[PDB]
Image (cartoon, rainbow, N blue to C red):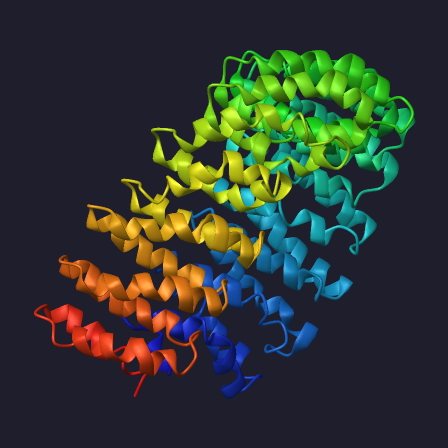
Amino acid sequence: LIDELRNEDVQLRLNSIKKLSTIALALGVERTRSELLPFLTDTIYDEDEVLLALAEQLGTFTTLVGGPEYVHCLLPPLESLATVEETVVRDKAVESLRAISHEHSPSDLEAHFVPLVKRLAGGDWFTSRTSACGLFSVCYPRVSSAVKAELRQYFRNLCSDDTRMVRRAAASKLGEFAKVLELDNVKSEIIPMFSNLASDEQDSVRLLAVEACVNIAQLLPQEDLEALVMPTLRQAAEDKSWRVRYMVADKFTELQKAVGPEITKTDLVPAFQNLMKDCEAEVRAAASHKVKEFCENLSADCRENVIMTQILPCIKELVSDANQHVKSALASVIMGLSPILGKDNTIEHLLPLFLAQLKDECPEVRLNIISNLDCVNEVIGIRQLSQSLLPAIVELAEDAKWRVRLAIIEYMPLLAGQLGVEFFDEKLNSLCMAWLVDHVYAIREAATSNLKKLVEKFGKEWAHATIIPKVLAMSGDPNYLHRMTTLFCINVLSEVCGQDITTKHMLPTVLRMAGDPVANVRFNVAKSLQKIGPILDNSTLQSEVKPILEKLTQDQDVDVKYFAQEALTVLS
């Protein structure tokens, strides 16, 4: 057990440490801290696999050390693991340090845990003091006034580090640190440091001043925002670095909720427009993702106007955007605007945009319209809207690129369900049957599964009268791969079609195919009988199934007669 530690075998060290919690159960819970932990301090240099396991383990060791009275001796090993120069084992040690901090009595905090934070924050290498930034949150609420005071100046120092990595780290935890301060220490300490990081030299730092900007916004009262936050947020949305502007757009709906319904109108609306018009496509994409969600969260009164007057004219220009990734990003959500703008406005203003997007070159655009028809269906009739859907459904189905075809096959059962039960027959029946003759297996395999879904949505009488005829007819296809497809179809169809239709129509065509010249088909005839065997009555099996299966076992091909008698496994 102890020998599994100092192994050279990589797997044996994992099952030794990932099972470390039960060695402390066996070894004295008193002995654990006097023997075990000393060894787990200054011997551990291994794979970043086992080190991620150790940090993980020490997070729960809180009880097995003797409870809160002896937590402070889980610190030396975790202090070492917050030094290792890996950005996964480090912030896993920070995980476990944050966890067991709550287990420290306020006196024990000041005695051990603060001193740790202090040392890590004064570390020579940056790795140390980047881990330190995470520890101020869990520390600060419970310690003394003097220690609070010290902890604040220690954070101010991390915020103005020499290295960008640290003041990146400091800005990323600036939100959580302000949440635990006092209202007018936020005004005095945080705001300046928030302002200072927001206009940092490196855009890698300024980046994190946006989701930090959100936090500082939620803590303040509305009055203060215009004074303290807004100037900073404004300079950000207009940052020269496009990555910073991306973050403003990425965190937009949550910036909206933070500044409340008032500044949303005044400042955010003009800013959103400016984002939807950004020179970098990444940003326009990001902003487009937030349209239905941002329009949703406008104040119940001044919204229906602002959407129509401020949001809409931008959208129109985005629909013609010279970037597929934008066009499609918008297309994904654009339709959720209907259960907000009502019936009348959708037909006048939203509808021509759907039809424009529907006749769009990019497949993934007009694909996204299809994925979200239920949005519009419940307030607008999918009636004359349908006329424009066909030319798009066909082009998606007949597209040279195969990943495109797999995509519309996916949406097909749901798309028939919201269209015409009958409409399907005239217009779409052709298209689904054509996917069974396809050069890609992935398409045929999807297309067969597709019609077993379609039976669900139309019942067995429909299948009997629309599909099964055309399906079976394929038994007479010159190429054996289409014949083979017929058997595969018969498998998935037999289950949803009952007994009478499977016995009287489907089974006949299966049995005939047993004399197929292509060996490859004959065995799939046997293998096919297995799956349809049970859904027959015990007489038809003895009648016409048993004699054919026996014939196939006397076949010249090795693998034919294999699957053949292996079917008589469910016979005799």
